[PDB]
Image 1 (cartoon, rainbow over the protein chains, first blue to last red):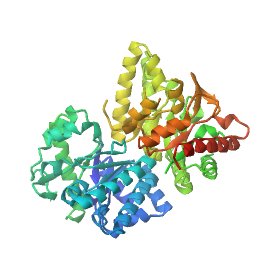
Image 2 (cartoon, helix red, strand yellow; image 1 turned 60 degrees about the vertical axis):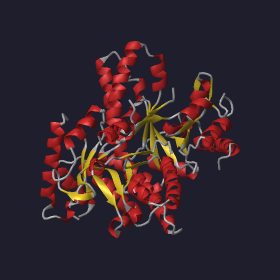
Image 3 (cartoon, one colour; image 1 turned 120 degrees about the horizontal axis):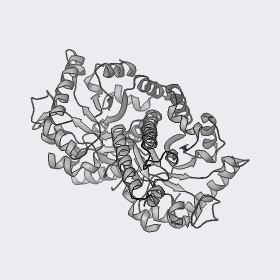
Image 4 (tube, one colour; image 1 turned 135 degrees about the vertical axis):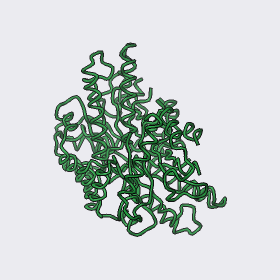
Length: 252
Length: 257
C-alpha cells in the first residue's frame, strides 16, 4: 500500500529537503501542489535544469512525485467568459502536462473541477466542456493521466476524495475501474479544509474496507495543510499513525 | 497534434542515447519507443544504476525528444505462464523492474509485446498461470501508476490497449472502433498474413488510409509509433526518412494533418 503526503503538509526548503523529510516520516511519495500562488505557478516556467534537479532529488531519495494537485484554474477557469484568461487556463494546462512529462508525474488531478462545474451557469459549462475536451486531447498526445473527483478516454480517470465525498461506499464501488488514486482527509458537511482526523464525519475504516474488498491496489495520499502549523512534522507523523491504524482496522 | 514516433530498433544500435534522440529529432520525430527485449544489453537496462537512468532523463529533457513507451518483449524468454516456478519468478522480477524503470525515466506506457499471441496459443494450464502473473503485474502497475497495455484481442485504469495495425491486419476496422476508449498508442507497420516482421511499407496487407480514417473518425488523439527494424540496414536514417514520408502521405489522404 503506497502512502503519500501532500506538499502543503510539510514546511515551506528545496525539493531535496521536502523529499528527505517525507522519507524520514515513512512516506513513499509526495503529491505536488500547483495552485494560484506565484511560487507554485512559476514551477510551470521552470528551466530544464530546475526540472532535472527535481528528478535527481526524486531518484536520490526514492521518494516519488507521482501526482500533482493542479488548482491553478481557480484563478484562470477553463469556462471563463473572459476570452483570454480562458486562453491562460488552457496554457496552464498545456504547461502542467509538459511539466508532468519532464519530471515523470503520473497523474494530474484537476482540483475543484466538479464544484466549479456544479456551480457554473449553462454558458460557462459549455465553455468548460470545450476546454476539458481540449485538455484531454493534449493528455492523449503526451500519454499523461488527468483525473477528477466523482469523453470516453483512457487518460481521463477519477481521483476521489473520501473526505469531500463524506461531507460514499457506492461511489467508490461504482468508480472502481477508474480510480487511479485516493485523497485521504477528514471533513465536516460544507467544511473541506484542515478538519483534524477523527474530528469530522468520514468513516475511514469503512472506506478502506470498501476499497480493499473492491480490489483497489493504488496509492493513498494524506491531504493536510500543516505547513502553517506549530511543528508540521509532528502533526504529519500523528496523522500518519492515525490513518494507518484505520487501515489496519480495515484489514490492510 | 499527430504525435509521431520511431522505434528504437529503426535507428543505429548501441547505448548512445543522446545520439539516438538527436537523430530522431533531426528526422522530425516527437519521440522514440525503447525496446527491452530478449538481449542482455537491452535487458540489462532494467539493472541500470540511478546514475545511468538519470543520464537518459537529462538527454530526453534536453533534446525534447520523449521516450513515452517501452516495447517490453523480454518475456518471450521468461514467460509468465511457464510451468517452471523459477522462470515464472524471473518473468515477474522483470515486470517489477520494468515498472520501476518506467517510474524512474518517466516512461508513460509499457507495452506487453507478444502477450496476445502467447495467450492465444497457450494451453489451459499456461493460460491459468499467465492470468495470475498478469493480475500481479497489473497490481504492481496500479501502485506505481504506470500504464501497461497489450494488443487488442481485471477492470483496471492501468491496463489498456496498444493495437498494432500491422498485426491486426494479418489477423481490423471493427476492433479499432470497439477499442477506442482504451487505445493509448498505435503501432504502425505493414505485414503479410503471418509475417509480422520486416515487411516494407506498401508490400503487405494493411490498408493504412482506412486504418487512419477509422482512428481519426473515432476521435483517437494519441501517438503513432512507426515500427521498423532498419538498425540492421547499412543506412538506417535514410530508410527511416523514406518510411516516415510514406506513412505521413497515407495519414494526409485519411484527412490527418
